[PDB]
Length: 327
Image (cartoon, rainbow, N blue to C red; front, side):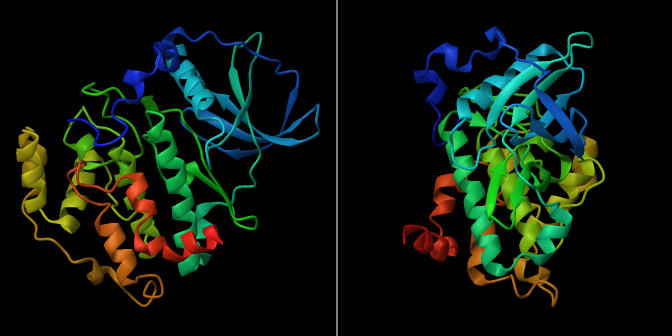
């Protein structure tokens, strides 16, 4: 399998651009950024709202947990490559501790409003607007030959008063190389696409479009974990109970995917449930025919069938956000 767009980005580019294992970090001074208050936790890091002793300007301090230096250089190179793009968190500095040798990345500051309290107040228009903004971010990184691989509400900081948005945490992101076989243990369980669950290793940028699709579904239907599985095998069962099992067979047969006996039996056979059956008094104010058409074109088992970030931005559903942006 090969991406349908931006497939040759790293083929035309000098190895310097994507060879991150050869990156030589030019650390700065941890003696220049002060911690103010923890704002986020994580399996690979801790986030802190900090201040820049110099400019006096606020900032975000990310302290990385202990991991192989390969994963640290990867996140750094990608952030350097993406700096400047629309709605991409901007990396400002890189520092480390002298004794512990603990790495720390310095980022622009963004208030960030907890999604479990924000999303419920979003209006029909707000949703169209913020998703459109996230798509600018994804089309940009895909155009630069990079997959984020961890798209979820937690990695999208939103300053709802300034209506500003940023895609964050590029700790699992990777460079896309046609035909390469990547690790399927990326992203958070609820946003993992079928390809990661059936073990299709040569996946591409379309993986991020499935994750986005799960996010979108969660918002219009007012049901955060839209696909709520307790483990990976259970995650695929949940997906198959909504999209139907016939579509999964086509997918499996097309890419000649095995699918072990346990997960297969575990999945069984299910008919497809039309999107409208998920509508209820709590979410009918957000479920329009256009929203349904858009979501439908995102959540497709076959990664090659999904809309690209660029096609998504032009969908009629964002019709007013575009006109407002134009003038």
